[PDB]
Image 1: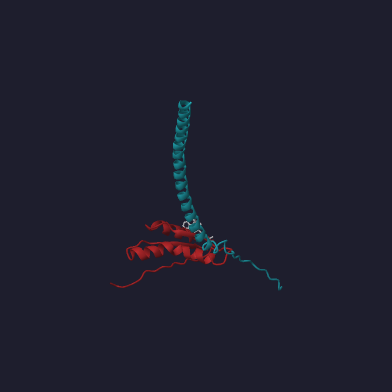
Image 2 (image 1 turned 90 degrees about the horizontal axis):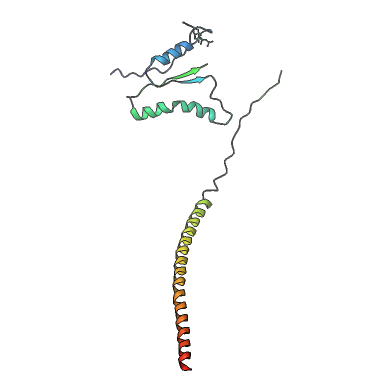
Amino acid sequence: QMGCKHVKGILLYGPPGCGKTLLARQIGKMLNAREPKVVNGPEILNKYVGESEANIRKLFADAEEEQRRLGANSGLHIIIFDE
Amino acid sequence: DMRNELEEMQRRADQLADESLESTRRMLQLVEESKDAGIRTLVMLDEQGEQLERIEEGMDQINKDMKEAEKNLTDLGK
Ligand SMILES: Nc1ncnc2c1ncn2[C@@H]1O[C@H](COP(=O)(O)OP(=O)(O)OP(=O)(O)O)[C@@H](O)[C@H]1O
C-alpha cells in the first residue's frame, strides 16, 4: 500500500580493530537466507581482457534468475565486500 | 624521477576451428553414404557367394552322372 522499495546498501568505516568484520559476519549469520558470497579484497582481477568484469557480473546471477522466476515471492541474497 | 613502470594484459588467439564446420558436415554426410553403400555391397556379396555354393553341387552331380552314363554305355557296347 505504501509503495516503497527496500534498501540495498550498507557501508562501515573506522579505525583498525573496532568490530566491523564481526558485525558483517554476525549479520550474515542472523538472517535466514542463502549462504552469503564473500569477496576477499581484490579477488576479481584477471590477466585476460574482459574476465574481471565477467567475474563481477557472475555474482548477480542467482538474484536475477530468482527475481525473474519467483517475482516478489523471493528470498534474500547477501554479498559482502571485504576491503 | 620520470621513471615509469607498466603492467601487461593478455588476449587469446581464436582456437583452431571456424573451418571445421563446413567441410566437416559434408565429410560426415559422404562418410555416412559410403557406409550405407558398403553395407549394401556386403549383403549382395553374401548372396552371390551363397548362389555360387548352390551352383557347385549341381555342377558336381551333372559331372558324375555324365561320367557314369558314358562308362555304362561303353561297357555295354563292347
Ligand atoms: N565490540 C566488540 N566486542 C567484542 N569483541 C570485539 C569487539 N570489537 C572487536 N572485538 C574483537 O576483536 C577482534 C577483531 O576485530 P574485527 O575483526 O572486527 O576488526 P576490524 O574492525 O575488522 O579491523 P581491521 O580494520 O583490521 O579489519 C574480533 O574478532 C573480536 O574478538
